[PDB]
Every structure is written in structure tokens, then in C-alpha cells.
Image (cartoon, helix red, strand yellow):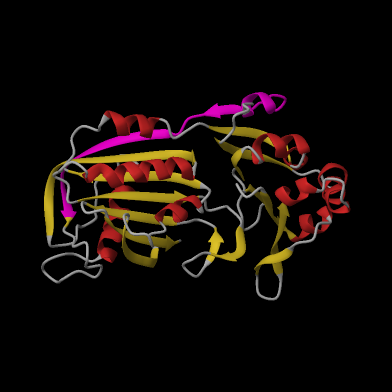
């Protein structure tokens, strides 16, 4: 975990793109937040934490099922649809992703890419050699002209030539006045409904860094740096989330100084296939956590993505390509000021 982007802004500022940032990070695996000096969690938040689902899981779902006029009209055009292959490593195994754009992006190896007969581009290189290819398919555009030679070629590839199938993670944010569930649509394949793992961990007597909202690199002996928080925050999670065997359950990390000891430390961790719309809701609540006066100096929101997701050629607003395992933090202060941190592994 190395820090790429570290910025300061305010949720009340027009220039703040915190909404766009969360929304453009589609595939989120782990969502965690930490509140210093907080004993009991509020009912408004606890309901929000307990309802970040649901998501779905389908075994060996063929790709031709995702390009039918049925699927496009039902899910893609009537809401934000999300999908990603499960237990398939990007460096070697094939990987497919469905963006809320409607774009079907599949990352294939050299052998598979040739067999599909689709036009894509070299993705990852091993020197002069080519290991991975990326094929992008816009199902929103293709829906306009399903009778085109483009579509039947792509259809023929998925159906007759090279019938690919994968284990898929599925989720759907509904903006539909006409309702039809995903459990019924994919009944022929044994689809499962799932709810994200919620883990509340209360830490006693926790040493926490002292921060200054307007000082990213801090003022020596007065407040810590944003970089120091980043490493400390990752260390806290590492000890609590690992839940080691009887041999390494003792924490070895150190807290940056100047610091402050906190009696009640609440630490929540949501795990599964979390939609960015749910994270937006969570971020909004944590933002307004300081509407009432609190004992907390600040709160933290952390989001980890999936390691095995396709990496497009389009770059984000921060100067690097979208996709892959993202890892960002929101350090929320009591005046709606926040720190935005991003990292790569």
C-alpha cells in the first residue's frame, strides 16, 4: 500500500467530486469505517450498515445471457447493473466485467482472445510478448441496432464459436417503475441471494493520531501527517481483520505522535459485493455525523476494491487508468472538511 493521491477538500464545496469518485469505483469488496470515542451505534446508521445488500452469485453463467435483448431492456436500461467474475485471477485467468455504462468488458488471454474472434486491444505485456487482451462491448449502443452485423457477429461469438462461461457476482441498483427481480430471471442457473458480512468491533483504550484539517503534512509536535494516518489506519485494520491463529493475535503496530488515547473505539467492516450507491449513502451519513456535537475529532471511511477486475484505457481525474484494485480513504472532520487518500498494491 503506497500513497498515490492525497488531497484536502470540503463536502460543502462545489469543486468536491467525492460523489463522482465513489460512483466511478464500481466494484467494491470491503467497506470499513472507524469512529473514535463512540460507544453505541445509532439506529439510523445501523439500518444503513445492515442494508448495503443484496447481491447475487451465479455459477457458470454463459456470456450470451448478458447480451440478449431481454437482459439489456430489463436490467441495463432500467437501472445501474453491476457484474464481475468470481475467483478468476487477472494475471492468468479470464475476467469479465459489466459496467453500469452497459459496457461489457472482458479481459482474455492470448489463446482465448483468438478463439473468440472479437476485436480488442493488447492489455498487459510481458516484455515483447502479449499476455492479456481487452474487448469492450457497448450494449447500450448495440441495443439501438440489434440487427446490425456488429451484434450478430458478437452474438455468434458468444453462442456458437466460443461459448464462454463464468461464476458471476451480480448486483442491481433499481431505478425502475416496472419491477422484475434477478432471482427469477436467472432461476435456470442456481442463483443465490446474498447479504454482505457486517462486523462491528469495539476497541478499548485505543491510541489515535492527532490531526489538523488544514495541514496535510501537519505541523511538527502539534499534529501528525496524512501519510502517517494512512499507514496507521491500515495497521489497525490489519490486526482486527486478520483474526490470526493463537500465534499472532498480539498487535505490533505503533501509533504516530502527537496522539490521544480513546476509551471507546467503534470499528465496522462490511464485506461482499457492495454497490457504490450504498457507499454514497454511508459516506453521506458519516459526513453529517458531526451535525450534532461529538467527542470524536474525526471519522474515517475506507473502501477496498477487487484485485481481479479489468483495467480500461481511460484515465480518471487523478491521472491514472481506471480499474484494478482501488483503495481509498475519507478522513472526515467536524467542519465537513475531508482528506482524500488513494493507493495501489
Q: Residue 64, how many percent across, how many down?
A: 78, 41
Viewer-proximal residue among 149 and 124? 149
Residue 248 visible in the shown view: no
For the N terminus, the quadrant is bottom left
Which range is magenta? 182-208
Residue 137 to residue 278: above or below: below
For residue 133, side relative to residue 3 (left or right): right
Q: Residue 69, how many percent across, how many down?
A: 77, 38
Q: Residue 155, how many percent across, how many down?
A: 83, 45
Residue at left 38%, top 30%?
A: 50
For residue 326, side relative to residue 198 (left or right): right
Q: Quadrant of residue 263?
A: top left
Residue 194 visible in the shown view: yes
Q: Furthest-bottom residue in view?
A: 128
Residue 28 to residue 202: above or below: below
For residue 141, side relative to residue 338 (left or right): right
Residue at left 65%, top 36%?
A: 75
Residue at left 31%, top 62%?
A: 9
Residue 275 to residue 112: above or below: above
Q: Residue 199, how many percent across, how many down?
A: 34, 35
Amino acid at each position: 500500500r503506497h500513497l498515490l493521491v492525497c488531497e484536502k477538500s470540503n463536502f460543502g464545496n462545489h469543486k468536491s467530486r467525492h460523489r463522482h469518485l465513489v460512483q466511478t469505483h464500481y466494484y467494491n469488496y470491503r467497506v470499513s469505517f472507524l469512529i473514535p470515542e463512540c460507544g453505541i451505534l445509532s439506529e439510523e446508521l445501523k439500518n444503513l450498515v445492515m442494508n448495503t445488500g443484496p447481491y447475487y452469485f451465479v455459477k457458470n453463467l454463459p456470456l450470451h445471457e448478458l447480451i440478449t435483448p431481454e437482459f439489456i431492456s430489463t436490467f441495463i436500461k432500467k437501472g445501474s447493473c453491476y457484474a464481475l467474475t468470481y475467483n478468476t485471477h487477472i494475471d492468468e485467468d479470464n475476467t469479465v466485467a459489466l459496467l453500469p455504462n452497459g459496457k461489457l468488458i472482458l479481459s482474455l488471454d492470448k489463446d482465448t482472445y483468438e478463439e473468440t474472434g472479437l476485436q480488442g486491444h493488447p492489455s498487459q505485456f510481458s516484455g515483447r510478448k502479449i499476455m492479456k487482451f481487452i474487448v469492450s462491448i457497448d450494449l447500450m449502443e448495440l441495443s439501438l441496432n440489434l440487427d446490425s452485423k456488429k451484434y450478430e457477429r458478437i452474438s455468434w461469438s458468444f453462442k456458437e464459436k466460443k461459448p464462454l462461461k463464468f461464476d458471476f457476482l451480480l448486483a442491481w441498483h433499481k431505478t425502475g417503475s416496472e419491477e422484475s427481480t434477478m432471482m427469477s430471471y436467472f432461476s435456470k442457473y442456481q442463483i443465490q441471494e446474498h447479504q454482505p458480512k457486517v462486523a462491528l468491533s469495539t476497541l478499548r483504550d485505543l491510541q489515535c493520531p492527532v490531526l489538523q484539517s488544514s495541514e496535510l503534512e501537519g505541523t511538527p509536535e502539534v499534529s501528525c501527517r496524512a501519510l502517517e494516518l494512512f499507514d496507521w489506519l491500515g495497521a489497525v485494520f490489519s490486526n482486527v481483520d486478520l483474526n490470526n491463529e493463537p500465534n499472532n493475535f498480539i498487535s505490533t503496530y505503533c501509533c504516530p505522535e502527537p496522539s490521544t488515547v480513546v476509551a471507546k473505539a467503534y470499528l465496522c467492516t462490511i464485506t461482499g459485493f457492495i454497490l457504490p450507491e450504498k457507499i454514497c449513502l454511508l459516506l453521506e451519513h458519516l459526513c453529517h455525523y458531526f451535525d450534532e456535537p461529538k467527542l470524536a475529532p474525526w471519522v474515517t471511511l475506507s473502501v477496498q476494491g477487487f484485485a481481479d477486475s479489468p483495467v480500461s484505457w481511460e484515465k480518471n481525474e487523478h491521472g491514472f487508468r481506471k480499474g484494478g484494485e482501488h483503495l481509498y480513504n475519507f478522513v472526515i472532520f467536524n467542519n465537513q472538511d475531508y482528506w482524500l487518500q488513494m493507493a495501489v498494491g
